[PDB]
């Protein structure tokens, strides 16, 4: 599913991501924009052989199981395929664990490089929330 901008903001809020660990909704929408362009089915293969999955490009080295990432963990206790669903529940619950891991949203390098320090509120501007 490719979400609309405000549609995704609303879904993220419904699932308790708004201001989670102090990160406003615009931060999460911005991260999703640059990680996946709002496409739940986004996948990308990393140089280390791990893969990133879903709207927030969650990585199989630590967070989910895909059966093809040697020496990896599955800390969210989910198949990576769950992160591709039109229902963002699994991605949100896993993101909550990731952002609580110590480095906040810096875990998403694209958030650090493209969202951090910017006017992230623009991502939810106009949205009925
Ligand atoms: Cl915001
Ligand atoms: Cl594996
Ligand atoms: Cl980047």
Image (cartoon, helix red, strand yellow):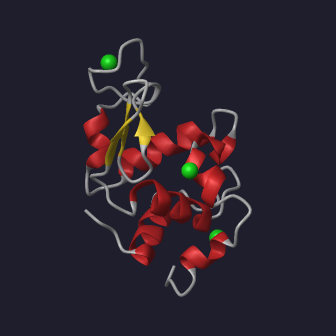
Of residue 109 and residue 78, the one placed in the foreground of this image is 109
Q: Which quarter of the rendered picture does the N terminus lie within?
A: bottom left
Q: Please state if 91 lies on the left or on the right of 127 as rendered.
A: left
Count of numbered marks: 0
Q: Residue furthest bottom?
A: 126
Q: Residue 109, image x and y in percent?
A: 59, 45
Q: Residue at x 36, y 14 (%)?
A: 70
Residue shown at 44% from the left, 25% from the top:
61
Q: Nearer the viewer, residue 94 or 41?
A: 41
- Residue 84 in view, yes or no: yes
Question: Is residue 119 shown above or below 33?
Answer: below
Identify the image quadrant of residue 23: bottom right
67 w.r.t. 5: above or below: above
Residue farthest to the top, as pictured: 71
Q: Position of residue 66 (x, y in %)?
A: 28, 27
Q: Quadrant of residue 58?
A: top left
- Please provide percent x and percent y for residue 110: 56, 51
Question: Residue at the spot x=48%, y=59% of the render?
Answer: 34
Residue depicted at x 31% and y 51%: 42
Residue 20 appears in view: no
Residue furthest front as drawn: 47
Q: Is residue 70 left or right of residue 128?
A: left
Instruction: Determine the quadrant in which ligand 1 lies.
Output: bottom right
| 27 w.r.t. 44: above or below | below
In the image shown, does 57 or 14 lie closer to the viewer?
A: 57
């Amino acid at each position: 599913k490719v979400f609309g901008r405000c549609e995704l903001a609303a879904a993220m809020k419904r699932h308790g991501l708004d201001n989670y660990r102090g990160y406003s909704l615009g931060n999460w929408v911005c991260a999703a924009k640059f990680e996946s362009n709002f496409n739940t089915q986004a996948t990308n293969r990393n140089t280390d052989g791990s893969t990133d999955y879903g709207i927030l490009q969650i990585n199989s080295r630590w967070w989910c199981n895909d059966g093809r990432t040697p020496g990896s963990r599955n800390l969210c206790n989910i198949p990576c395929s769950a992160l591709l669903s039109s229902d963002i529940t699994a991605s949100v619950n896993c993101a909550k664990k990731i952002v609580s891991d110590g480095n906040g949203m810096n875990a998403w390098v694209a958030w650090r490089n493209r969202c951090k320090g910017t006017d992230v509120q623009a991502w939810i501007r106009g949205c009925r929330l």
